[PDB]
Image (cartoon, rainbow, N blue to C red):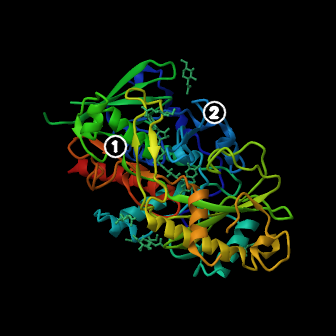
Amino acid sequence: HHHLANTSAHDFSYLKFVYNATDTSLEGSYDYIVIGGGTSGCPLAATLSEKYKVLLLERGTIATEYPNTLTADGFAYNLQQQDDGKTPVERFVSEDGIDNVRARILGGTTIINAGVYARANISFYSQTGIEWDLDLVNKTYEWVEDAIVVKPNNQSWQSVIGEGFLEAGILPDNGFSLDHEAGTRLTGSTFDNNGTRHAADELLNKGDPNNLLVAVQASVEKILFSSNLSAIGVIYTDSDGNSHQAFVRGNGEVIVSAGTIGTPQLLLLSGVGPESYLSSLNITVVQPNPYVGQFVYDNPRNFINILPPNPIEASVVTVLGIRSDYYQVSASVLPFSTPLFSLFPTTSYPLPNSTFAHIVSQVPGPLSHGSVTLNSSSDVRIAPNIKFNYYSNSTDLANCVSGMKKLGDLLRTKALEPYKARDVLGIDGFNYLGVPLPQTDDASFETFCLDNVASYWHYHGGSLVGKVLDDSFRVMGIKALRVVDASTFPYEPNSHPQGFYLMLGRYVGLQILQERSI
Ligand SMILES: Cc1cc2nc3c(=O)[nH]c(=O)nc-3n(C[C@H](O)[C@H](O)[C@H](O)COP(=O)(O)OP(=O)(O)OC[C@H]3O[C@@H](n4cnc5c(N)ncnc54)[C@H](O)[C@@H]3O)c2cc1C
Ligand SMILES: *[C@@H]1O[C@H](CO)[C@@H](O)[C@H](O)[C@H]1NC(C)=O
Ligand SMILES: *[C@@H]1O[C@H](CO)[C@@H](O)[C@H](O)[C@H]1NC(C)=O
Ligand SMILES: *[C@@H]1O[C@H](CO)[C@@H](O)[C@H](O)[C@H]1NC(C)=O
Ligand SMILES: *[C@@H]1O[C@H](CO)[C@@H](O)[C@H](O)[C@H]1NC(C)=O
Ligand SMILES: *[C@@H]1O[C@H](CO)[C@@H](O)[C@H](O)[C@H]1NC(C)=O
Ligand SMILES: *[C@@H]1O[C@H](CO)[C@@H](O)[C@H](O)[C@H]1NC(C)=O
């Protein structure tokens, strides 16, 4: 933990090589084009720029345009803000009926998220069967952590929840650790101890400022292709609606880093995907693959809200209670009269009048899956349809039951006892915002899980390694095309995956360079 970042202002030095996509002089040949300046995309583009000419295209603007993205205090504002098509938070509703968000900004979802930093479960690497260079993975985590991760200072509510998890049997006590392991710990945060947000856009500062160019408000609409099928470039439009082209040259590559939703969407619009589906939309099939936009996952969030009779201090999540079958945390949150879109799964949810503890459990995997399909067959700015099929797999429901029973145990701890409105024996002594925990039968817990599910926001899949990609993240059947982002895996790396996806952008960047050099 020598390596971690210090308290520091958000480093915008990289803006010296950020340009409006309206600039036609960005058009031309590069060694690499990275689509999506997000969690994976920014460290990938920065890494490739050490040796080669890179163009990073991001649909959103720069985070300075939306100052409430730059502090812990600002987190609520960004989810409360109406989506006018330019804001850093893009709102959507799954076909399941569950409200959700994705980022639209340079730095991607690291500019809007809850700041929690963790490394992958060390068993994840062997689970994938990918031949990881595990020494390099660990060097890559330290490169991220040196730049943007701190050891969080103590927060009253997080310490209460930590004592509660330990008392409720989420053992052992792991103290301060970045590692995803069974038990209770303080993990890292991308919010510094002054409340400054640090994010994936800062990793652009590790890029070579003579090799890296970033275009913002660059909406990438199509991947361009070469009978030896290759990606050759992209079409992108600017904020005025004019079209632009860029190309890769020589042994260069296009990498799609547009997220679980953006990646499959762009692959389908470009004619990569299921043959009968694309041919049903009269989209010319460049590469038939049945799995583009298939195996899309959203880990369920289930929760209760308690309203302590004395105010609690608002906190960012730093304390985690991990078991193999559920991952638990709690935020303490100020009251509001404008809802945080997707905090609760629909717009019809009570507003809190006082400070509340949002106490949550995450279902691992999950095993339930759905898909991304096109709404428009031409317009990338029209959000695709996304369905997660929450609790379609009975294992997921069984795991939520275990998690909700454990939150029951948590509300019974001496740790939490001071936060009750009534000094009675039962957890009905708490005041609840919304639905409280339900008897000695699983069926009431099942109904609670099914009825009150929300998004954890850690959705993943749609371009899986083993289905769309090979073990080098290449799109099977296409040269000079890769995918690096959360679309690539069908299970979580851990409870809080930003750490893994930040590492993955640089790691795959280093594998591309090593491949090159031979
Ligand atoms: C509200 C919220 C809170 C979260 N909290 C945490 C947490 O505390 N800790 C944690 O570990 N994880 C958290 N997560 C999850 C984690 O942040 C994400 O899973 C991860 O950041 C995803 O990275 P990505 O690179 O796949 O996508 P992104 O970071 O979203 O990057 C994709 C980028 O592509 C851009 N893009 C999309 N389509 C196009 C296109 N056609 N042309 C150009 N650009 C395009 C997008 O604007 C975006 O910048 C949270 C998620 C959300 C939504
Ligand atoms: C890009 O230029 C247009 C004017 O042509 C302007 O409306 C837009 O806000 C600019 N975007 C950025 C990110 O500077
Ligand atoms: C990588 O770091 C983890 C701690 O996150 C450690 O458990 C593991 O042994 C390291 N692996 C290697 C190959 O050094
Ligand atoms: C800071 O955080 C935790 C809370 O108990 C603990 O590690 C440490 O003793 C605390 N120090 C304080 C409150 O000064
Ligand atoms: C870590 O990953 C492996 C599955 O790959 C799993 O068996 C184990 O339960 C996970 N542990 C936790 C605590 O999530
Ligand atoms: C597009 O999304 C809308 C919601 O605006 C949905 O109701 C409509 O039927 C969808 N169209 C297609 C082609 O999926
Ligand atoms: C749930 O998940 C696995 C796929 O991972 C599958 O084997 C099982 O049949 C699925 N559905 C169930 C058990 O309802």
Image spot of residue 341 (x, y percent):
64, 44
Residue 178 visible in the shown view: no
The amino acid marked with disc number 2 is Glu
Mark 1 lies on a secondary structure that is loop
The amino acid marked with disc number 1 is Lys
Locate the N terminus and report the quarter of the image it occupies. Answer: bottom right
Left or right of 136? Residue 216 is right
Q: CA distance from mark 2 to mark 1?
A: 31 Å
First in sequence, mark 2 or 1: give its number: 1
Residue 452 visible in the shown view: yes
Give the camera-side residue of 54 and 280: 280
Give the camera-side residue of 261 and 372: 372
Mark 2 lies on a secondary structure that is helix
Q: Nearer the viewer, mark 2 or mark 1?
A: 2
Which residue is under mark 2?
Answer: 65
Image spot of residue 350 (x, y percent):
74, 50
Q: Quadrant of residue 87?
A: top right
Which residue is under mark 1?
Answer: 51
Give the camera-side residue of 332 and 210: 332
Q: Classify 253 as above or below 486.
A: above
Disc 1 crowd, CA 10 A, few/some/many (<14, 14-19, 20+) = some
